[PDB]
Amino acid sequence: RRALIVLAHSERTSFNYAMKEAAAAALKKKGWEVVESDLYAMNFNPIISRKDITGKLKDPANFQYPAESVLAYKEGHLSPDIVAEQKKLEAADLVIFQFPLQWFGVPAILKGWFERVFIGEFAYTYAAMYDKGPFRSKKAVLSITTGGSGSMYSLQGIHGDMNVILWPIQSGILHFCGFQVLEPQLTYSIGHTPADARIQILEGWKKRLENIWDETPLYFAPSSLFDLNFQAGFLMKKEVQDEEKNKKFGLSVGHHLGKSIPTDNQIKAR
Amino acid sequence: RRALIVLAHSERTSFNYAMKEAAAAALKKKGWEVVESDLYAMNFNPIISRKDITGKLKDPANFQYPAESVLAYKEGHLSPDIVAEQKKLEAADLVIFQFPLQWFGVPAILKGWFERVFIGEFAYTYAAMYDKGPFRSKKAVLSITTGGSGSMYSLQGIHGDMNVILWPIQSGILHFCGFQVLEPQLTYSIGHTPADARIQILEGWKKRLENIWDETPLYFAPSSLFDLNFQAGFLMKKEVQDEEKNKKFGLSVGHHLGKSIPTDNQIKAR
Ligand SMILES: Cc1cc2nc3c(=O)[nH]c(=O)nc-3n(C[C@H](O)[C@H](O)[C@H](O)COP(=O)(O)OP(=O)(O)OC[C@H]3O[C@@H](n4cnc5c(N)ncnc54)[C@H](O)[C@@H]3O)c2cc1C
Ligand SMILES: Cc1cc2nc3c(=O)[nH]c(=O)nc-3n(C[C@H](O)[C@H](O)[C@H](O)COP(=O)(O)OP(=O)(O)OC[C@H]3O[C@@H](n4cnc5c(N)ncnc54)[C@H](O)[C@@H]3O)c2cc1C
Ligand SMILES: O=C1c2ccccc2C(=O)[C@@H](Br)[C@H]1[C@H]1C(=O)c2ccccc2C(=O)[C@@H]1O
Image (cartoon, each protein chain N blue to C red):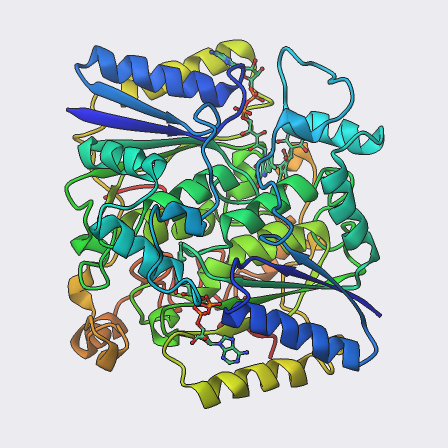
């Protein structure tokens, strides 16, 4: 029912802004309740600081952000801007991340949003890691625009596999917190695209969003395959290790196991 | 003879600050000229904006950061803070990036530093990308500290291969600009390390820096293996494609070619 669009672009004149508006309008049309987070427009502070904890710190002499931020969440003393974003996430069923690819990742303003908003207990638990994480009932999507062509990001392109680039965001940030990660919306070489083709990209994104919730998510190795505790080193179960010995391919981009990475692990489902 | 230490930590009480001081002292002792970039202390602005261009914009109606930033570099009207950092880089032979791992990547403040400082024509060109790029005569190192243990980042750990996490920074940011990327200094689960062991870590980092310049850099596929033109799609040369058909392993993490990733591609040189 509810969706949150997080946008990491400065210009209203950009294709990224167009893609945000396309999504918002498409979803609203299909009966969704759409909430935005235009990070630049919000003049969002992306830097984690002691200013994110409203009152007195627990140990001001040796400030440690994870410890202090959790305490601030639990005691209700987080910075109001963080709290507002946290309330937006709690509410949302679908979370869309609309951004241009910058230095083979998320723009610094989005990275800062994750660091400041995805606080301990709220977003993650060392116990409730990955598929067990807080956002297990939510679904996330990355809608990316790149300057480089798709062939550059193919297995034989100079930049190398796009699946490798996506892994730290999709597994490390999103899946880590519980999210079911849906296929990314990859819009390559947008600067080279003529006007009519751009108008089509938008129509395609809108038609996708008509049934985005019914889609099958990307594959990540289930937490059930690992002995989750410090004594075991959070390693794959010895039984799973044995079962996988006779298997031709790895499980995911990170769990490639020095075997082949299953084709488009981070780009495609099934 | 010149070195630059870029530090992405708020607290002087941190092990990251200790590691910065350790490096600075070690290098200075071995006759190096050491310059710092304590991003938090500098109160560095990590957000790319039109405020990064002091002169008249080319198209203020449709602002495009890459195009305008290059023009500002060439015409000499980039933001003085950006210029100061650019002058530091121009001077440095060795560049050390001291930071805690945050959300499987660089902290937002460092990410913003790359986005705002690594401007087109200064840090890279279309022709001068990867080996045979502007910083080809420089060497870069990542000194990372993590909360999670090394086993979590092993091929069998929950987070998966650390080599996959490193790839977008080491290849995508550093090697893309010509830097020879040296073996990363990975300091795992630093919070759990006892005092005597923490001392040993610092002493080891200092002893490494005694002969850091003479080290062999990490392997990245040379640009000479690819037909770097639009007609060809920036793909590997037909002869390279064929030669690498009978080879068990891929070239790198990103150039895995659907085969096995060579062990510790992004961690070791062998
Ligand atoms: C610091 C930095 C780092 C970067 N790193 C990378 C990298 O690692 N990899 C990479 O591949 N690229 C990289 N890039 C390039 C970047 O990914 C692209 O420039 C970006 O994705 C372009 O998208 P945009 O929203 O800015 O579009 P724009 O360039 O602003 O817009 C594209 C076109 O769409 C048009 N448009 C706008 N609205 C609409 C609409 N409603 N309907 C139709 N057309 C519309 C515009 O008028 C324009 O002609 C980097 C750029 C920067 C600034
Ligand atoms: C937003 C955020 C995201 C994170 N994401 C991740 C993630 O993706 N993966 C991950 O693994 N971790 C993650 N972490 C954890 C983070 O990487 C670590 O907590 C961090 O690396 C700890 O290093 P530190 O510099 O902060 O040292 P500290 O927190 O200060 O601890 C180091 C210890 O060494 C002591 N010490 C200080 N100076 C010296 C000295 N001179 N000699 C000896 N000992 C000294 C200190 O007193 C302390 O006991 C995240 C943390 C944050 C804040
Ligand atoms: O910003 C860019 C970049 C920066 C770092 C790594 C890869 C990249 C890219 O993919 C290239 Br295409 C580059 C941009 C780029 O340099 C550029 C310069 C002048 C006009 C337009 C552009 C772009 O739209 C490009 O996106």
